[PDB]
Structures are given as C-alpha cells and as structure tokens.
Amino acid sequence: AIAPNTRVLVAGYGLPAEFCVTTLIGMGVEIDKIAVATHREDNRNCGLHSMLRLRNIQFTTAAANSEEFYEFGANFAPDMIISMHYRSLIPGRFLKLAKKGSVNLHPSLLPAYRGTNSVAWVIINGESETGFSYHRMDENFDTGAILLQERISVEETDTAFSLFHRQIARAMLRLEEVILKLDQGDPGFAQLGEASYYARELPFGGVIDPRWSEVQIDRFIRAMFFPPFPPAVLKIDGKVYYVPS
Amino acid sequence: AIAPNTRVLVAGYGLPAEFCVTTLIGMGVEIDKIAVATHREDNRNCGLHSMLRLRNIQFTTAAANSEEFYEFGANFAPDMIISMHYRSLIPGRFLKLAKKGSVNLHPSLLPAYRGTNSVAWVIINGESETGFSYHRMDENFDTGAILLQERISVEETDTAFSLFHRQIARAMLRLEEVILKLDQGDPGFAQLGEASYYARELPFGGVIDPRWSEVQIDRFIRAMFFPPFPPAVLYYVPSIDIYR
Ligand SMILES: Nc1nc2c(ncn2[C@@H]2O[C@H](CO)[C@@H](O)[C@H]2O)c(=O)[nH]1
Ligand SMILES: C[C@@H]1CNc2nc(N)[nH]c(=O)c2N1
Ligand SMILES: C[C@@H]1CNc2nc(N)[nH]c(=O)c2N1
Ligand SMILES: [Cl-]
Image 1: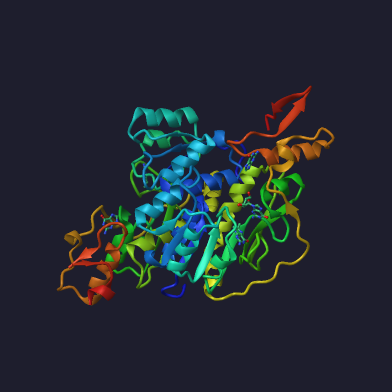
Image 2: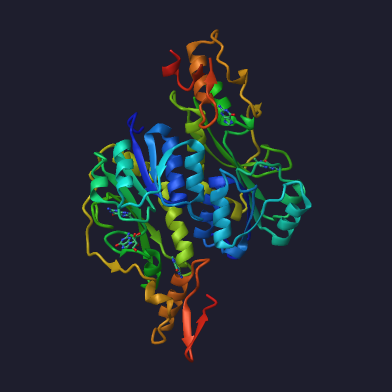
C-alpha cells in the first residue's frame, strides 16, 4: 500500500490522467491529498475536468510556466508528482516541490525517441518493437531516470492511431506499480544507450516524398493515420491529395 | 490478435467505456467497426462523448428500450457487444444481434451482489473480499455466464469511493483479455454460488445507529463515503476518526 497521507499531484490531460486519478483513489489516496494540474477544458480533457469538479478535487489550468501554477503546487505540497500526458514542460522548481520526486509517461523506450510524435516515428522508421517509459522528470524533456519500461510490438498493420491507443492502454496496466515505486523511493536507473530525437513538427509536414520506397511510403501512410486529422498528403502535378490510407 | 474486421458495439458510460474504446483502437479495431451506445453527455460521461465526437465514432444515446437503440445496433451489425457500465437492461433482441454474444462488467463476484451499489453493500456487510465479473449477458441483469473474475481484497480503510475506483481500474486491466475471450467464443461458465441482490439506496437513510458495534459503524461510515454525496449522519460523519 501507498504510505498513508501521501499527497499526489497529477499533472495531466485526458484519459490517462482520468485513469491515474481513478487509480490513486483506488489505492486509498484521500481526495484532499490529490491535486491536478491540467489544461483548459478541451475535447480530450472533458472527462478529467468533469471528474475533478464532480469529486471536488482541487485543480489548476494555469500555464506550466506561470506563477499561479507554481503557487498551486506550493500550497498543495505534493509528496510526488505524476505527469500523465501533461503537455508542457514542467519547471524544475515545481518538480523540486515533491520530495519523493516525479514520474512521467513517455511512449517510447527512452532514450530512443526523445521528442514528440514518438509513435509516428517508430512506425516511419520501421521499428518492430517500441515500448513505454515511466521515468522521473528532470528539468528537460525525456531525460530522467527510468522507473519502469515495457516493450510493445509494432505490427505491420499498426497506425499511429492504433499504436498510440495501445501505448496508453498497456501503460495503464503498470501505473499502480509505478506509483508504488515512487512511494518507496526507487531511484530508478539512468537512461542507457544512444538517444534519438524527433522534432515537434509533424513528420515531413505530413507529405509523402516521392523518392521514398514503397515500404517507406506504406509506413508513412500508417504513421500519418490519426483520426480526425488529415492523412498523409501526396502532391501530384502541383496539387494536394489526401491518401486513402 | 482479434479477428480482422470484427465489429464491436460498446454499450457503456464514462471512463470504463472510454477505456474500452481506447483498448479496441489499440487492438486494431477500426473506427468504422466500433459503435457506441451510451447515455447523455453528463459529468461522468463527457470523456466518452468527447472521444466519440473527436474520433467520429458513431454512437447513440437512445434509450435501451427504444426502437432507435435497436435500429442503431441492427444497422451496425455487431459481432460482439461489450457493456461497460451501461446502466440499462439491454433487450434480448438487441443482444441477439451479435453472433459472438456479449460481455458486461459487474463489480462483484457474481452471483453474489447482484444489483446496484454493490461496492457500498460489500463494505456495509463487512465483506473482506469482493471482485469483478465479466459475464456474458442474457435477458436478465447479472445472470449470464462468467467469462472472467478477479478478486479484490476489501481493506479496513476502504470506502465505497476507493473500492468503486479500484474496481474500475483493476477491471480495465483485464479487459483486453476478455475481449479476446469473446473473440474466441469462450462460452464461460454458468454462475454458481450463493446469490444475493442489493438495490439502489443504502439503508438507514445514511443514519448511524448508536446501537451498532464500532465495527458496524466504521463499515457504514466507509460505505457511505463517496464524494460528492453526503456522508453518513449521526452531524455529517465522513470517517470513524471524526466519529469518535
Ligand atoms: N516529450 C517531449 N515533448 C516535447 C519536446 N519538445 C516539444 N514537446 C512538446 O510539444 C510542445 C512544443 O511546442 C511542448 O509543450 C511539449 O508538449 C520534447 O523534446 N519531448
Ligand atoms: C512529457 C513530460 C511533460 N513535462 C515534462 N517536464 C519536465 N520537466 N520533464 C519531463 O521529462 C517532462 N516530460
Ligand atoms: C449491467 C448490465 C447492463 N445491462 C444488462 N442487460 C442485460 N440484458 N443483461 C445484463 O446482464 C446486463 N447487465
Ligand atoms: Cl463480491
């Protein structure tokens, strides 16, 4: 069991954050010992936002770099911070508020696929294996010590869509164990191997390079499939076509 | 892996439904092979509705006993139906649409704690263990064949609140397995054991009887604890700590 009176601050967004809050409640963390930092109510965040209002869990939507956010953290005085698809870089001083530190879920086997769009890139690059990494947060993205990783096979029929959702689902299986590792002061291990990096931008601006091989085009089309967003674009005779995927 | 082109209708509500759709998408079920029947958008169902809108997943909020609900299922032609906290009785003729049948998640070890508010009665009644049952649905609530059960210990500090949430979390962790049972035509097993049934309201209109033992009082307090609902009353008593 988690230490009694453990104070947990969840920074997050959407279903993973809703699930994390559910998990914490299920672990017996009291409502007054849960706080959430999230973003302004969205499509993807209606679930979380309504849950927080309904249960009277304190929350902020202040920007991560704002004073209000820092005060929210400070007044709460978390023991631990759990980032569950929180979009923004969390300032180091906010992290320092939690003397048991923090954990964040990243959908790659770090230090591979640092950056964003990790699911799309894994597919673009023809990986047959990827995974997720619950890792302590340091002041930069994607760099902190690994608390838990798990491998996820990439199938030749996976899309960014299917892999993204499997990533979430599979990662949720491990969440309770991760919270316990935090609870118990598991230092985790410094990330190992060579880091790869991918830019915030949509891969190749969503545009198929005609010089790619068919295998690379197939991968890219899959990597680009993510309803409701536009699919991969093919330009022909100066004109845009969305692929059927 | 789930059979290609399997068509899945999720009848559900709130996070368990959202998690189910997420699980399906991860399993490679395409959006046009998912349909959702749910209830209106509300404070416990907006996450699901937002997902359905964002991903353009076809859905209905028609009442379970309505022609519109039936026509939604018939049009979609599910292979399987997954009920994830769907409140209402799904009519037999709707279940009949899915050749691979259905499963529903019920937060007890069926046939114990049929009915509603199972988590609160589990605590009131002093159970030391409970669990969840993924069971095929027949025409009645809570009576169909068991596909999967998992036991959950009920701790001395558990409240209706914590147990309700742990039920969901733990049950979600078995969902993928259950969907694959459905896919594979696992017949499950006929329910066996001591049936019980509890409905709706906890007794005593939330009122602590000082004749009860401290063990009874503590259980009642914990069973009544479920933000944002009022707690047990003696004046409002949200913990035994406060009670003493
Ligand atoms: N995880 C991760 N996210 C990033 C990185 N760079 C940018 N982002 C995300 O995309 C936004 C940049 O506009 C940030 O707020 C992050 O949400 C990175 O290196 N790692
Ligand atoms: C994805 C998350 C969100 N924000 C983070 N903030 C810091 N500081 N460090 C991080 O690693 C992360 N990753
Ligand atoms: C809880 C769920 C919701 N609806 C059901 N409908 C039928 N027919 N059979 C059922 O068992 C159930 N249980
Ligand atoms: Cl039970």
